[PDB]
Amino acid sequence: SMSVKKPKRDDSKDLALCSMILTEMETHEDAWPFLLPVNLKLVPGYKKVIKKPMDFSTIREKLSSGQYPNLETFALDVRLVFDNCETFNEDDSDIGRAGHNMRKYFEKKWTDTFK
């Protein structure tokens, strides 16, 4: 509350550390469904169904241009990429499996870097 603060967690490396996590997600062999925005002209249903499209290239641009106010807003966009994937793709598909794999990979890097 006013004039009453928890001890100050060092957040000065968070930008760099989120950038490294993102590089590792970009270079995973199962990243291919997530590297670029879904083409809304060429994928029937996507525009209407997925209210908030997100992909790695869009996170990378937001990161590089100071559009994440803190590391939690960054995690929310990464998770949004996989939540969208689950909404639109069957579990038993290459893309559906890719998303489960990448979400796992992300959550481990996230815990090991920050928790």
Image: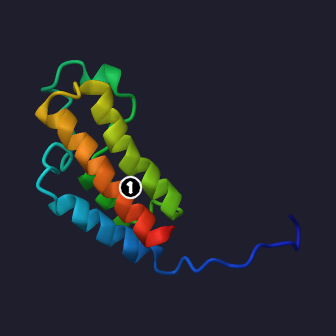
What is the crowding at mark 1: few (fewer than 14 residues within 10 Å), some, or many (at least 20)? Answer: some
The spot of residue 88 in percent (x, y) is: 27, 26
**What x and y, as percent, mark residue 23?**
24, 67
The quadrant in which the N terminus is found is bottom right
Q: Residue at x 39, y 46 (%)?
A: 79
| Residue 36 percent location from the top left of the image | 18, 47
Rendered view: 3 above or below 38 = below
Residue 90, by quadrant, is: top left
Residue 48 falls left or right of residue 66:
left
Image point (18%, 19%), residue name? 44
| Residue tagged 1 | 107
Tag 1: amino acid: Glu
Residue at figure coordinates x 16%, y 36% from the top left: 95
Q: Nearer the viewer, residue 70 or 108?
A: 108
Identify which residue is drawn at 23% across, 28% down. 91
Place of residue 5 in the rendered image (x, y in percent of width and height, measured from the top left):
80, 73
